Structures are given as structure tokens and as C-alpha cells.
Length: 158
Ligand SMILES: CCCCCCCO[C@H]1O[C@H](CO)[C@@H](O)C[C@@H]1O
Image (tube, rainbow, N blue to C red):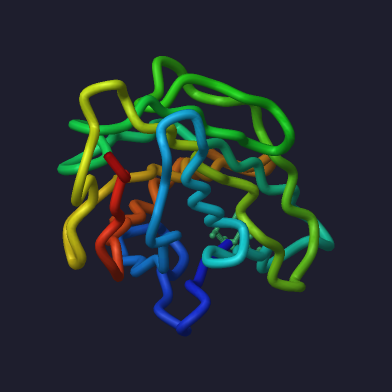
């Protein structure tokens, strides 16, 4: 089991960490959602599907900078919604193919009432998402740490 980003940055067998740079909607009004869809950015595969079934969870999701300060978040994992920053590990997603399959994570961030102006700064850390991978074969338990960075400023109109 290993993962890679849309630009080819990889995390090999045994886990580790990688930076993900995301393009964000430039304008988000109060009452609207800023969608950070990581399913188009993070892809994983099973290296031995003939014998092993891999299990993948979103172990934890943390918010930073402008996202922590100016937004109220929700994380959608494989069709279900949870608070963001996260309060529990999600259920498991099965990886049973060598074909690169998306990690089904998407953040839904709506501005808090105090938000106005530049709510997210270009180049800043916005989130840390921990992918936890286990299997039905041995005691392998690995963390794939995704550091999410904003590629651009996000303005909340006033
Ligand atoms: C002859 C037996 C060969 C055993 C090969 C072990 C491969 O382990 C990796 O791939 C697995 C499947 O994706 C992951 O559950 C854990 C490791 O990432």
C-alpha cells in the first residue's frame, strides 16, 4: 500500500508525510462553502490485492491558520459527514486494487460571522490530514500524513 498526490509526490510502503498544495475558490461569502476536495489530489493503491485487503481511515483532521481562525468545518469521508477539526477516527474504506483510487476526503468550510477580508493566506498551512492504513493480513498499521497548503488567498466579502 502506497499513495501519491496529483503532481506525483509520493508516500511509499510504511507511510510518512507529504505536502499537498491546493487551489481554492478566491471568494467565499458568509453562508457559502469553501470546498477542499482532496479526492482529486490524493490517490492510493493496494500492492498485493491477490492476498491482502487494505483498510483506510481518516484517523484525524486538524485545522490551521486562516481555516482554524475564520471557518466552521465539516469533513466528508466516503459519503458521510463529520466535524472538522475531527473528534473521532472514521470507519474504514477498502482498497483491493493496484489501480490508483482516490482517497475520498473533502473539507466543507463556511466562514464564521467574524470573518471578513483575506480569510486564508496564499502559502499557509490550512490542514493536516492523517490517513491510517491497516490490513487483514498482519499487524501493519501506518500513518500517511498529508500537510495541506493554500495555493492562493481566499477573500470573505464584507
Ligand atoms: C510473500 C508475501 C509478500 C508480502 C508482501 C507485503 C506487502 O506489504 C505492503 O503492501 C500491503 C498490501 O498493499 C499492505 O497491506 C502493507 C504494505 O504496504
